Image (tube, rainbow over all chains, first blue to last red; front, side):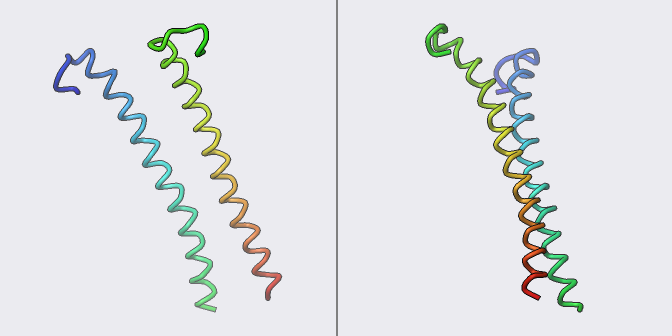
Length: 48
Length: 48
């Protein structure tokens, strides 16, 4: 895209990709945080 | 939106609804993970 257009146009198309990929990454990180808390409970039980 | 807009103009209005509804569904699904992790600990105490 950014290859065919002009900074002014490339920008409007690049912003939708930025918006989608940011949301993807945030979903990944939230679901890792919820799963690490489940692994910590297991490791505390195994220590006990 | 599919009755008082032509297809090139209804895409822009349908996307605004899609984004909002996706956000709301994903908020629902995060808060259920966080509530289920709490019910799980209560059931683990009941089993003990």
